[PDB]
Image (tube, grey):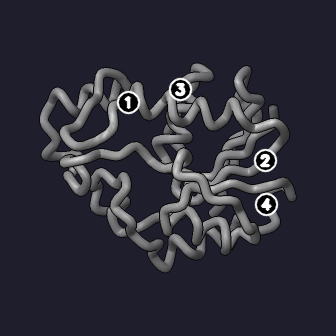
Amino acid sequence: MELWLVRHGETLWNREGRLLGWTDLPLTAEGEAQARRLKGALPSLPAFSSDLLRARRTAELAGFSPRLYPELREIHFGALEGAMWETLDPRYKEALLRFQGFHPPGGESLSAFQERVFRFLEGLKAPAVLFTHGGVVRAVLRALGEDGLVPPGSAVAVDWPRRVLVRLALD
């Protein structure tokens, strides 16, 4: 199934390097600019989006009217919400780097996050554009055997659950 996954535009925490999960931050001026550039670059397909502000706003500025699904939200970092990557305990840094064995207090485990994301993708019956988060795109790319890091406001199209089709970044 052709699916286009879009990483929302940047927020202040991108430059600051803080774990951004369910904390509902707004896009920055540049973030909104990134979203606008996506308009006309994404296919005209049914759209879905994380219900968090930054994702919804990206979808809007990209020219879509998506149906909201919390299942497309970034992982819930719990007590680690807002933590600077830099100061993150080695055990947590490693878990996030290797994308495994991560269960922050008061948050969501990486295994539960993957289950949530993949269950949502499984339910899609036809091609669609998904406005989501870095961790979601990462989970998908990693499951397809590729490096999952993509720039804010960029997109990736995949043939789920078989392969990556294209990565699109705009300047």
Labels 3, 2: front one = 2
Labels 1, 4: front one = 1
Q: Which residue is mark 3?
A: 142
Q: What is the crowding at mark 2: few (fewer than 14 residues within 10 Å), some, or many (at least 20)?
A: many
Q: What is the crowding at mark 4: few (fewer than 14 residues within 10 Å), some, or many (at least 20)?
A: few
The quadrant of the rendering that contains the N terminus is top right
Q: Which residue is mark 1?
A: 110
As drawn, the label of residue 128 is: 2
Going from the N terminus, do you reach mark 4 or mark 3 first?
A: 4
Labels 4, 2: front one = 2
Mark 1 vs mark 3, CA separation in Å: 13 Å
Labels 1, 3: front one = 1
Mark 1 vs mark 2, CA separation in Å: 24 Å
Mark 4 vs mark 2, CA separation in Å: 14 Å
Mark 3 vs mark 2, CA separation in Å: 20 Å
Going from the N terminus, do you reach mark 1 or mark 4 first?
A: 4
Q: Amino acid at mark 2?
A: Ala
Q: Amino acid at mark 1?
A: Leu
Q: Residue at x 13, y 36 (%)?
A: 89
Q: Which residue is mark 4?
A: 41
Q: Residue at x 60, y 31 (%)?
A: 119
Work out whether residue 125 or residue 110 is closer to the camera in this orientation and state it. Answer: 125
